[PDB]
Length: 91
Image (cartoon, rainbow, N blue to C red; front, side, top):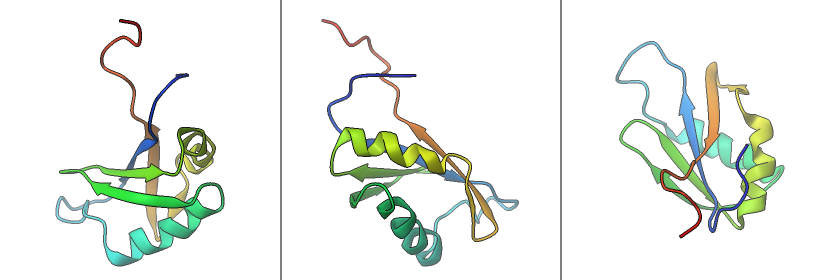
């Protein structure tokens, strides 16, 4: 539950067993792209130390893709989550 955000960066993680598997491969990504297309047309993708961020054309689009929150793909449970603002919105 968060409204207001100038951007469109969403966090995406995959549930695995080994610590050297948390890394996203060509399949996990390639496949994801399409899945995200169903709602928003991905434009930029940023890989985090352990997490995986994904940018979208607009912020709203990143709100629709949330429908993939938890969706399991390639025998790998994916968990999507918006990037909550650490600091207050007002100024």
